[PDB]
Amino acid sequence: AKINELLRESTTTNSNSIGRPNLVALTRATTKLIYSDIVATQRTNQPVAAFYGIKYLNPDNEQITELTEESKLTLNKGDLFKYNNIVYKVLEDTPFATIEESDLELALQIAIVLLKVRLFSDEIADARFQINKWQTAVKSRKLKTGITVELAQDLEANGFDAPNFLEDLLATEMADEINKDILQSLITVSKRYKVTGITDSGFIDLSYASAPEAGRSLYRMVCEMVSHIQKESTYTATFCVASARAAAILAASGWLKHKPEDDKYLSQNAYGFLANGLPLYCDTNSPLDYVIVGVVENIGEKEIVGSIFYAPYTEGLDLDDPEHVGAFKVVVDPESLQPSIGLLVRYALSANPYTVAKDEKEARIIDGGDMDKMAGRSDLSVLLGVKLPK
């Protein structure tokens, strides 16, 4: 029976000796429901997972002149200067003169067009990035289903109307647990928004002073966060996460559309595609009414750019059927007069230690899964708190 083959396949370690169809199937069932996309996944086959992530920061502090409002007035022909990490060269004496624009950046942008200044890259270069490698213990979550094997057995027989419901039920329970761990870690790890007084005297309120509109105010907020992202790290947000209220209807008024076009590329795990384009995942179960904007990017086949790293455990490719089986397993619950069902769920789930640990020697004192320490600084994700009506 399904339940049985699942127990006996789950008992064997190293999934390369014998094929395990029920488990592969159940793994495929589970992985379809996990919000992988919003985390930097790195499979692991060790009791301790090895993570790798890249990140940078504005250094330097010829001493290239940083551009300021009163700095631009002294620049002469041949002077070097930099703005937003990019260094320019002056082609004419005292530029920005004929430029009436009062906004610094804007002025500099039309300064580029008028050939007044020019970008500069004219011989060894510093590190523009920094690969970090750390380790966290892969956790072993044990979930009591309450389902006796007895039921799970007659459930097959008494289930002509819903063939592999057992599979769906389980896949659903493991996925939910991990999706919970993820959403939870992102809310705890992600940074806040710093717009004039911690988002103008408390993290933006859009209720009392707001009509039941199409929720434009919210969407605008999201765009600014996407900019603020590449503005502090050139990578380009890839995802969004919101509340069930803040998204299921609020932004769902012209700015969120459940699937733009028939299979136009979007995981059915994503609530809807945003007017902006980046996919949005609905939290539904978190008591916040908040929105988070992050990026999960990769170099090659490895996803090294993320707020949260996910390392499901693996016992190796089924080798009978190409599939990493190990992260999910079914066991028996020994705490019951009637044998129940237990789901073994193994995976690491860390943050980048180096989001706080300055030196490499400090990294072996603080842990990435130390959700207490990582709380606050991530940069690759930003959370916005929201207050809505009823």
Image (spheres, rainbow, N blue to C red):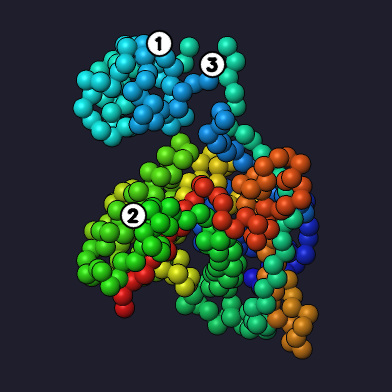
Residue sitting nearer the eye, 198 or 277: 198
In the drawing, what numbered circle is on residue 130?
none
Q: For the residues marked 2 and 1, what is the alpha-carbon distance in whole angstroms?
A: 40 Å
Kind of residue sitting beneath label 3: Glu
Q: Residue at x 32, y 12 (%)?
A: 93
Label 2 or label 1, whichever lies nearer to me, is: 1
Distance, label 1 to label 3, CA atoms, is: 12 Å
First in residue order: circle 3 vs circle 2: 3
Q: Quadrant of the C terminus?
A: bottom left
The answer to whether mark 1 and mark 3 are in CB contact below 8 A is no
Residue 83, relative to residue 379: is it above or below? above
Q: Residues within 10 Å of mark 3 (few under 14, many from 20)?
A: few
SS at badge 3: loop
Q: Tell which circle, 2 or 1, labels the residue nearer the N-terminal end.
A: 1
Q: Earlier in the sequence, mark 1 or mark 3?
A: 3
Few, some or many C-alpha atoms within 10 Å of disc 2 (few <14, some 14-19, many ≥20)?
Answer: some
Give the residue at mark 2: 221
Residue 66 pos. (x, y %):
45, 27
Amino acid under label 1?
A: Gly
Residue at the location (72% across, 64% down)?
A: 140
Q: Residue at x 60, y 27 (%)?
A: 127
Q: In this picture, is 134 found above or below 256?
A: above
Please say whether residue 159 is visible from this viewpoint: yes
Residue at numbered disc 1 = 78
- Which residue has dot 3 on it? 62
Q: Is residue 259 left or right of residue 190?
A: left
Q: Are marks 2 and 1 in contact (CB under 8 Å)?
A: no
Estimate the x, y position of residue 25 in percent, counting from the top left: 59, 60
